[PDB]
């Protein structure tokens, strides 16, 4: 007779789950036509290779492809308490074929697609480098795009997040359904090489100072943080000695992350359109923080590229009220199969713990996995390289130089450790 909360059962608490989708790159021009140079503006005059209703490898995403991905999520049977969405909604077309109003129109379409299909789902977006006109020129003060997305994303974000988003394209937000968890959505496009607006700025839009203060508050309030952004930290795995953002910013951002590794329970990025792992470590090789780069929904590649990705979306599992990452489930669309019969079959690609025989996604568990990759003829690395392209090409091979570049980028996010890895393994 005293109104005490009702105790749950002795059952095991169910894991928490969240979706990650990225790099949708809608091409509204997509349409099948005899002259394959007119199928999609994003092929920039090249002949689409073998186009179908769900797209083509030389094209960005038809609306039907993006719809099939979100329909899959909706009907998947997976419970999820939120979704992260790390940017890049307009297609790859020349700057004069876009405008601020066109960019805002595509972002609106994608946002409203999500809000219409998932009316009760909190979504945490980040801006990508194509989410601005002209592309990559994301500014260090308020702008029409920043104001537009602050209005579009208001259903998901509190007043403070809306205020920082409008001013600089970044925010942090407590997760309604997960007390003790905070999402930090960075604008890492401010650090991206092509951005003229941030040349020679030590702290563009004051995001480093803001990030430092946010993480410090999280540390003292005993919160855990998931970092999300479009462009990742670290090195490109397919090129030699090339940081994904400007070296000065990569070093500075990584030092913040190392200092707050006890608070940061995950980092999630897009932009590369590939499935990649990174493990942030200290100078002595001790693992500190796990990093997950998710592949894109668009399958687009340039004519000069041999390989591309299949469309992908992914799901993370985490410990409730604790937020340690337990697993990752990668789903994909076999685009050639879907196009041939005209019906999509989004399906499981792999479960990380099962594919690699690891216990969970903690930095030490993944560090031990990537150490296996480094062994000669590692079957684990061969599997990883197949998944890097989301199973696009089972016959794709990675020679000695290719593999050194991959493994060095997985394990060494800062310049000193990366260059030392090259010294040892080139
Ligand atoms: C996504 O869905 C696609 C479409 O179904 C799958 O791609 C098909 O995969 C099958 C099997 O891997 C392919 O069938 C085999 O093709 C081999 C030829 O390899 C390539 O080279 C020729 C060049 O002429 C291309 O035309 C061809 O499309 C391939 O890209 C043949 O060697 C095989 O024949 C022999 O082996 C098999 C046993 O393995 C026997 O069944 C045969 O009778 C014969 O003895 C076989 O024909 C098929 O070609 C692929 N189609 C396309 C369009 O690429 C993907 O595998 C799937 N993705 C995933 C991850 O599952
Ligand atoms: C885009 O493709 C057209 C058509 O390509 C042809 O059709 C393919 C299915 C295949 O049979 C190719 O070998 C063909 O080229 C290209 O125009 C045709 O190209 C060849 C050589 O010029 C010739 O057979 C046709 O007369 C050409 N013109 C037409 C109208 O068919 C065109 O060059 C391609 N464009 C680009 C940028 O690659
Ligand atoms: C990180 O925060 C600590 C803790 O300070 C408190 O943390 C939050 C609740 C926030 O709301 C702050 O206002 C609080 O004061 C800071 O530690 C303080 O450091 C100064 C020296 O600069 C010292 O005089 C205070 O006594 C310290 N307070 C405590 C409680 O130890 C620290 O400065 C913050 N770090 C950064 C980089 O800003
Ligand atoms: C997002 O864009 C898609 C594609 O442009 C819209 O679906 C199309 O809507 C127009 C009508 O305005 C038709 O011309 C197309 O045939 C529709 N389908 C496709 C596959 O193109 C969709 O309505 C837009 N959604 C929102 C919320 O704006
Ligand atoms: N996987 C890759 N292999 C080779 N070149 C790439 C690869 N990814 C990107 N590039 C190159 O890096 C630059 C950025 O490419 P984008 O397609 O815009 C990535 P996004 O669409 O996420 O912004 C391009 O010049 C592109 O040619
Ligand atoms: Zn992209
Ligand atoms: Zn990008």
Image (cartoon, rainbow, N blue to C red):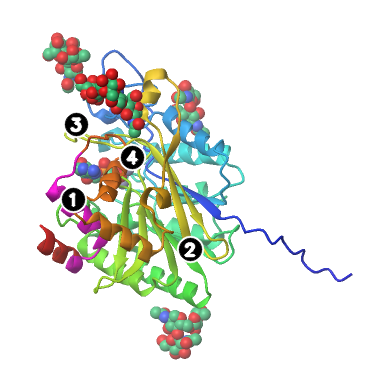
Looking at the rendering, the stretch of residues picked out in magenta corresponds to 397-417
Say which of 323 and 96 sits in front.
323
Q: Quadrant of residue 290?
A: bottom left
Q: Position of residue 238 (x, y in %)?
A: 19, 48
The earlier-in-sequence mark between 1 and 3 is 3
Quadrant of the displayed image that contains ligand 1: top left
Foreground label between 2 and 3 = 2
Q: Nearer the viewer, residue 167 or 184?
A: 184
Q: To which quarter of the image does residue 359 belong?
A: bottom left
- Please name the predominant secondary structure of the magenta segment in the image: helix
- Cα separation, mark 2 vs mark 1, equals 30 Å
**Residue that carries the numbered disc 2 in the rendered image:** 324
Tag 1 residue: 403
* Label 4 or label 1, whichever comes before in sequence order: 4
Q: Which mark is residue 390?
A: 4
Residue 376, percent across and down?
Answer: 18, 53
Instruction: Give the CA distance from mark 4 to mark 3.
Output: 19 Å
Q: Position of residue 400 (x, y in %)?
A: 13, 49
């Amino acid at each position: 007779h005293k109104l005490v909360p009702l105790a749950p059962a002795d059952r095991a608490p169910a894991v928490g789950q969240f979706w990650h989708v990225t790099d949708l790159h809608l091409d509204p021009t997509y349409h099948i036509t005899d002259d394959r140079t007119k199928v999609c503006a994003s092929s920039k005059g090249a002949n689409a290779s073998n186009p179908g209703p769900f797209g083509d490898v030389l094209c960005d995403s038809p609306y039907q492809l993006i719809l099939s991905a979100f329909d899959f999520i909706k009907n998947s049977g997976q419970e999820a308490s939120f979704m992260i969405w790390t940017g890049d909604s307009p297609p790859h077309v020349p700057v004069p074929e876009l405008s601020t109003g066109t960019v805002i129109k595509v972002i609106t379409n994608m946002t409203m697609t999500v809000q219409n299909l998932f009316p009760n789902l909190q979504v945490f977006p980040a801006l990508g480098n194509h989410d601005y006109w002209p592309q990559d020129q994301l500014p260090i003060v308020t702008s029409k795009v920043y104001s537009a997305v602050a209005d579009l994303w208001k259903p998901w974000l509190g007043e403070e997040a809306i205020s920082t988003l409008k001013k600089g394209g970044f925010y942090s937000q407590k997760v309604a359904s997960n007390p003790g968890l905070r999402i930090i959505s960075l604008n890492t496009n401010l650090y991206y090489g092509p951005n003229i607006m941030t040349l020679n700025k030590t702290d563009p839009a004051n995001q480093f100072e803001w990030l430092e203060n946010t993480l410090n508050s999280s540390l003292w309030n005993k919160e855990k943080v998931y970092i999300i952004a479009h462009v990742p930290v670290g090195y490109l795995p397919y090129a030699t000695d090339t940081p994904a953002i400007r070296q000065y910013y990569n070093e500075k951002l990584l030092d913040i992350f190392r200092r707050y590794s006890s608070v940061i329970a995950g980092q999630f990025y897009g932009h590369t359109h590939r499935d990649s792992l990174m493990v942030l470590s200290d100078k002595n090789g001790n693992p500190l923080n796990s990093v997950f780069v998710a592949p894109a929904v668009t399958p687009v590649k340039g004519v000069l590229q041999k390989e591309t990705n299949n469309p992908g979306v992914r799901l993370f599992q985490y410990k409730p009220g604790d937020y340690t990452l337990l697993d990752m489930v990668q789903y994909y669309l076999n685009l050639t199969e879907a196009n041939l019969k005209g019906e999509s079959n989004w399906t499981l690609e792999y479960v990380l713990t099962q594919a690699y025989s690891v216990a969970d996604l903690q930095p030490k568990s993944l560090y031990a996995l990537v150490q296996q990759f480094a062994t000669k003829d590692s079957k684990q690395f061969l599997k990883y390289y197949h998944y890097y392209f989301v199973s696009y090409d089972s016959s794709a091979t990675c020679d000695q130089h290719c593999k050194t570049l991959q493994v060095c980028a997985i394990m060494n996010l800062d310049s000193m450790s990366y260059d030392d890895c090259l010294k040892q393994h080139l």
